[PDB]
Amino acid sequence: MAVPPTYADLGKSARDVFTKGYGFGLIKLDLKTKSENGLEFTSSGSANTETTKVTGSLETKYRWTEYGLTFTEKWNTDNTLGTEITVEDQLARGLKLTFDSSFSPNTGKKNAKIKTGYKREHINLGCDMDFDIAGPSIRGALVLGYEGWLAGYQMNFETAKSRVTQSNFAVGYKTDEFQLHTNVNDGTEFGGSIYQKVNKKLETAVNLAWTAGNSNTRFGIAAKYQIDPDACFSAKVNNSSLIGLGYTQTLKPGIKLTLSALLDGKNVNAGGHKLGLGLEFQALE
Ligand SMILES: NC(=O)C1=CN([C@@H]2O[C@H](COP(=O)(O)OP(=O)(O)OC[C@H]3O[C@@H](n4cnc5c(N)ncnc54)[C@H](O)[C@@H]3O)[C@@H](O)[C@H]2O)C=CC1
C-alpha cells in the first residue's frame, strides 16, 4: 500500500530470463506457503538423477500482521543451519531491522550479522553488517526511486581494511511499453539489459555484459510466447551461437513445472544436448 518495491524493479524481469536455468540434467523443487497466522512454510531443494547429487533445504518463515513482524529461518539438513528475524518499527514507520545468525553443524563456528535500514515511499535504502571470525564485512544497499526513473546502488565495504571489498551498481528504467534494466559488477564488470514487449503476444528481452580490460563481450537474446493455457513457451540464444529453450507450464494447483534445454551448436551435433528440470511455485487453497 505504501512504498512500493523499487529495488526489485531494478532488473528482476531481465535477470529472471537472463539467468538461464543451469541444465545439469537434475530435478529442482521449490514450494512456498504463507498464511495470515504467523506460520510460513518454505521448502527448497534439488535432486540429481543422472548422478548422486541431491540436497534438500528447509526454511521456516513467519508472517504476523500485514507489514509488521516477519521472521525468516534457513536450515539445511546437510548444509549449514541458520535463522533470521525481521521487525518493522511501529512508532518509527519506515525503520526496518533484520538480524540473521548462521551456524555450522558439528563445528561450533557461529556467525552473527545485523541488518538495519529504512524504507521511504520516495526511496528505499538499507545498511547491513556481517560479523565474521576471520574478518567481518559490511554490505550496503541503497535504492533510489524517481517518477519513471529508477536507480539502485549496492556495495560491500571491507571492514578488515579501510576500503570497499566489492562494488555493485544497477539502473532501472520504466517506460510505457518499454523496459530497460542495466547492471554492472564493480568497476571491472559492466553490462546492461533491454526488454521490449510487442503489441501482440510476443515478448523480447536482451542481456549482455562486458569485462573491462579485455575485448570480450557476451550478449544474449530471450523471448517469451504465451499459447493460451497455463503453459508458456520461451526461447533464448547466446552470442556463442547457443540455442536455448525454456518451457514454463503449471501442473498441479500449487506447483509449476519449468523445463530448460541448452544446445551449444559449437559441438551439440557431435556432442549432446543439455536438459534441466525444476518445479517452483506456492502451495495454496
Ligand atoms: N540468453 C541467455 O542468457 C543464454 C544463456 N546461456 C548460457 O548461460 C550461461 C550463463 O549462466 P549464468 O552463470 O547464470 O550467467 P550469470 O552468472 O551472469 O547469471 C548471474 C547474473 O545475474 C545477475 N544478477 C542481477 N541481479 C541479481 C541478483 N539479485 N542476484 C543474483 N544475480 C543477479 C548477476 O550480475 C550475474 O551477472 C552462459 O555461459 C551461456 O552460455 C545459454 C543460452 C542463452
Image: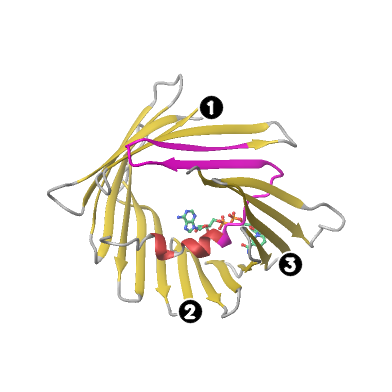
Which colour scheme appears in the figure?
A: secondary structure
Q: Earlier along the polypeptide chain: callout 3 or callout 1?
A: 1
Image location (x, y in percent) of residue 99 = 29, 38
User: Looking at the image, which is closer to me, 169 or 73?
Assistant: 73
- Amino acid, disc 1: Asp
Q: Is mark 3 within 8 Å of ligand 1?
A: no
Residue 41 image position (x, y, % from top left): 44, 36
Does the stretch in magenta take in 32? yes
The residue at the point 41 percent across, 64 percent down is 9
- The residue furthest top is 106
Q: What's the mark number on residue 258? A: none
Residue assigned mark 1 = 78
Q: Is residue 169 visible?
A: no
**Ligand number 1: quarter of image:** bottom right
For the residue carrying disc 2, how many other residues have a C-alpha within 10 Å: few (<14), some (14-19), or many (20+)?
A: few
The kind of residue on which mark 3 rests is Ser
Look at the image and give the residue range highlighted in magenta.
17-46
Q: Residue at x 41, y 70 (%)?
A: 172
Q: Earlier in the sequence, mark 1 or mark 2?
A: 1
Q: Which mark is residue 241?
A: 3
In space, the residues marked 2 and 3 are separated at their CA atoms by: 29 Å
Q: Quadrant of residue 131?
A: top left
Residue 72 within the magenta-colored segment of the rendering:
no
Near mark 3 (Cα within 10 A), the count class, few <14, some 14-19 or many ≥20, is few
**Callout 3: helix, strand or loop?**
loop
What residue sits right under mark 2 in the picture?
A: 177
Label 3 vs label 1, nearer the camera: 1
- The amino acid pointed to by label 2 is Glu
Question: Residue extending furthest right?
Answer: 270
Q: Secondary structure at mark 2?
A: loop
Q: Residues within 10 Å of mark 1 (few under 14, many from 20)?
A: few
**Residue ID at (28%, 60%):** 1
